[PDB]
Image 1 (cartoon, rainbow, N blue to C red):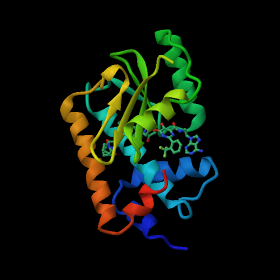
Image 2 (cartoon, rainbow, N blue to C red):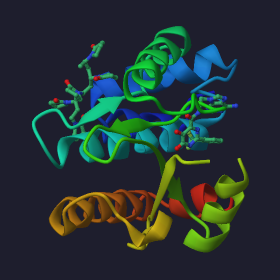
Image 3 (spheres, helix red, strand yellow):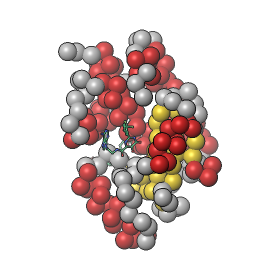
Image 4 (tube, rainbow, N blue to C red):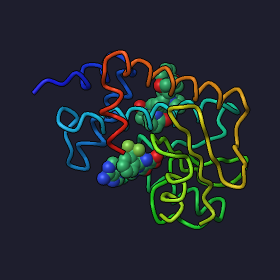
Length: 177
Ligand SMILES: C[C@H](C[C@@H](C[C@H](C[C@@H](CCN1CCCC1=O)N1CCCC1=O)N1CCCC1=O)N1CCCC1=O)N1CCCC1=O
Ligand SMILES: Nc1ncnc2c1ncn2CCNC(=O)c1nc(-c2ccccc2C(F)(F)F)[nH]c(=O)c1O
């Protein structure tokens, strides 16, 4: 079957991001043309990660999300043996060289509180959550980045939810997380 979600995801997100998302979904055994809300979510999580890496220095962040499983773990191993940090139990999204810590990025359609707390159970790796309605929540209220960088990310999330709304896809997306 041919989605409206799939076609919208394709002409909304950047072709490289769509491809990286199709690769990750297929690696975990899922179909972008079947579970299309997950398709949109993966693209969003990716793009937010990339803007995050963009705000800041020239190369302050090492990008872990996007890479293939094996290579991502390789890079975190090299970081851990370089900075002396505990090899996380689960793959993070980035590493801050300035603050010497792995960052887990979060993008949720629930309360920033419940998604944080649920993710917080999954220990020195920073957590940072964003939301489609413009809210964010981060560990020790250390939001790592400039106010403008985070503002731009929030604006993007909101325009995405607007673009889904006018296509009547927003509600189906929301009642799925
Ligand atoms: C470096 C490239 C691709 C890079 C993805 C993005 C490009 C995006 C990000 C900007 N943004 C922000 C808004 C949404 C978006 O896409 N783009 C698109 C427009 C121009 C640009 O830079 N990055 C980030 C770092 C520099 C870069 O190239 N990856 C993929 C995962 C790891 C990684 O580093 N690698 C790495 C090895 C294989 C490969 O191919
Ligand atoms: N069963 C699986 N489904 C998708 N991905 C799987 C995966 N198993 C392994 N991975 C890859 C490792 N995942 C991450 O690193 C990571 N996962 C998420 C997340 C988690 C659950 C449901 C949806 C999401 C997402 F937000 F992407 F859509 N959010 C993040 O921010 C993040 O960094």
